[PDB]
Image (cartoon, rainbow over all chains, first blue to last red; front, side):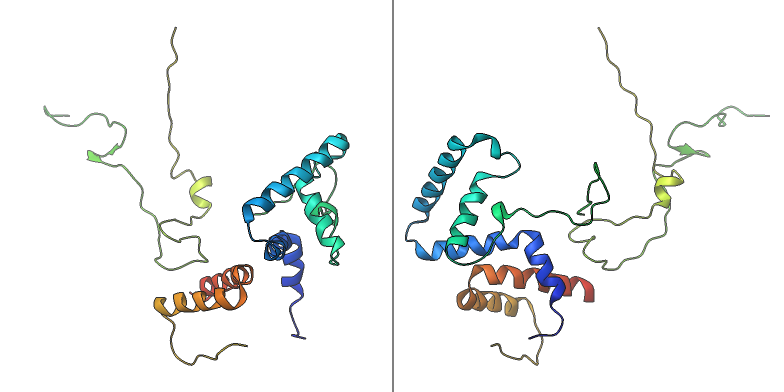
Length: 97
Length: 63
Length: 45
């Protein structure tokens, strides 16, 4: 185990790079990319048609993708959504320079 | 006393009878954390709070 | 598993390496490697 990799790992998860890695795994199972884009789009539509009000800050496309990964054994949060543990209070915004 | 042709008042962008379109500032030429990549400049806040580069702009709207 | 280089890196050499890394590890890994090398380059400069 390399000794000091902690920050980089926190950041990869926090940044949203996890999603990028996932898209790649999933495309390693497919001959046509174009078809996979069409399959994911259809699933998202079914999800929004069935429960409309859940979505809006939770995005359907993200939900379809997280669900695929969790089925195959990698724990991912639902819709790749993470809270800010340290926000000062309501109505406060982080400056992500 | 004034002789004909001598200056009485100065206009904008002119000081003491010469054209003055800019200011003189302390500068260094070096790389800084990527803020200067390609052609970009990093500047101090002094310029903002001492008003070195402030300009007035007037527009007209008519009916 | 990488080579240890004891001679200088110029632009031709970086293109060859990015190419070689894309083939061995794939585009996802290479993107992270690239962001990290950028930071090191800006800092040293």
